[PDB]
Each structure stands twice: as C-alpha cells, then as structure tokens.
Image (cartoon, rainbow, N blue to C red; front, side):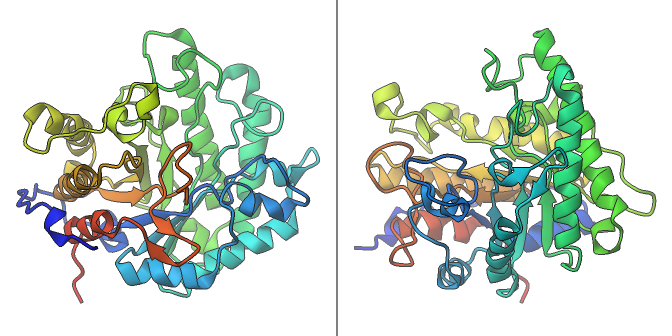
Length: 380
C-alpha cells in the first residue's frame, strides 16, 4: 500500500539566485524524466529492422498515454536520449528519414502536452561510426557533430523554446583508464577536455547558423563525461554564442552520487544504506552541488542535472529519503533534476525502473511524490 509517511519533512534554506531569464527558464522546467533505454539503444539480440532499436532494450513502444501519465504526475520536462550512429549512412552521415520521423512523433507527444523536451546525441562515442574526443579523431568527430546537428536543427526548425538541444551526452575516452573520471594529471584527458570544448563550439555554431528559432533556443553542453568536475575545472570553456544572444547556454551534469549507493550493485560491492541524518552521507550529495552553485548558479548561469537516481536494492524508505533530499538541495541552489528511468524491473542489471510503461503507472510512487514535493513550485 502507498505509505506517505516515508517522505521526509525538509525545510532547506533557499540560496540567493539572480532573477534573470536563464534561471527563470530552468525553474519553469520544474522536474524532468528520461525516456531511458529507448531511442538510445544501439544493439540487441533480435533486431529485425531499424525501428526495433526503440524496443530493443525497453521492451515496449512509446505511446502518447505514457507521456500523458508522466505529465499528470508533475513532471514538466522529458529528456529523450537518442543514439543516432546506427541510423546514419554515407560520408555525409545522412540520418534515415524513417528514424527521424519516429523520433519527431515521440517529441510531439511531449510538445502537445505543453511540456519541455531535451533532444540529444547519446551513445555515439565511436571512432568509426560517430565521434571520439581525442586529437587523432577530430576530423571525423567534427564532421559527425556538424552533419548530424545540421540535420536535427533543420527538421525541428519550427519548434519554439520548449525544445532544447543537448549536443553530446557523456563525451569521454572509451576504453581508457580514465574513461569515467577527468584525472587532470593525465595528458590524454586534458587533450580530450580541449577536444570536447571544440566539439561543443562546433555544435553551437552549426545550430545557430540555421537561424530562425534555432538562433535563440537554449542549448546544453557537458564537460568530460558530464561529471560535475568536468564542468567546474579550469580547462572547461563555455562556447562562444552569436552576438545578440545572452545566457542561452546551459551546463549539463550527471551525478549519481554517491555511486556505491546510487548505482553500484550489491553483488559488486555496493551498499543499500544512506543516512539522511549523517553529515558525511549528507556531504556525499551536497559537495558537488556547492561547487555548481559557486561556479555557476549563484552567478545566474543555468545548470541542469540531466541524470540522477538510485537503483532498487529493496530499500524503499532509504530511496525516498535520498531522492527527496537530493531534489530539495538542488532546488535550493536553483538546479533542475531529471530522473533516469530505464523501465527495468527484471531483477537483473541496473534497476532504474520507476514508471511501469506496461500499465502506465509508477511502481515506487513514494519516491516520485517526494521528488515532486521538493521540486520547483508552479506560479499558476
């Protein structure tokens, strides 16, 4: 049965945030949800045609009713991860119209619900088929980013500010020892960071060049592996935007912190405990948020935590407390949170399933109600 008593009573002091267009835009997004393991799937056991990629990992085709349910809960933003590499051909990386049409269909489900949508490139870090953030691969990487974004920009040219473009997901050195963390002492990672700065710049230039609504829409840019440190380190450089635009670039960060609790499986040495009353455990959540506040939000530059969440370890209460605290602390610093939901309830793999797409209802409602309770308020 639903147990509302699990949700903690929190009164976190609001920090000072500038009253500008950028920060107000983010407040309007309110709280987001990821259409995880869907259009981002890039392989599978039984894919007969290209459209099967949508159900390959998710196991079910997206419908309008699903999106209606998400909105009804209180979410006002849907992030739609898309891996374009298995749907591109030729030296010009032409995107299949069949794939593009389907993506636009799902985007429309959200837009018709007056929601905000974030469209990105996801699992496209591939030396041969996509981009790879290292100097040896800059030629192909630039061609990939510019070709793909010119096409996406042209297709969605008529959509207003409700549609946001996220150039890259978690650009990193796949296979490298420092694939999952920007070790600033490593020569290879510094080269990668510089390459990422260049690719973010190319992404912005390409989109802006198409003019119209593309010239003024908000764009998101991540640092190395979209980590908080990748965005706060001294090597990170915000892209130069066209003259006339002011504060239209949003910093993207992903933070499943602390990892041993939020994502590491029990079988792999993870833990299922996190104490909201323990200062050390509290710090595991706020440390990166303070860095983000000091470097960006306190100064009026928007930041979005595009991915967050905690895997199911048969620890409902602890997860309700953790997610509630996480969202409340982010809100106090003007930061938006977007839940990662992969529809996985199989008891195996990464259990980031929350919304049961089969029955169109949330399986751990207390967690999501706690998040809605502490997210940005709605003025009318």
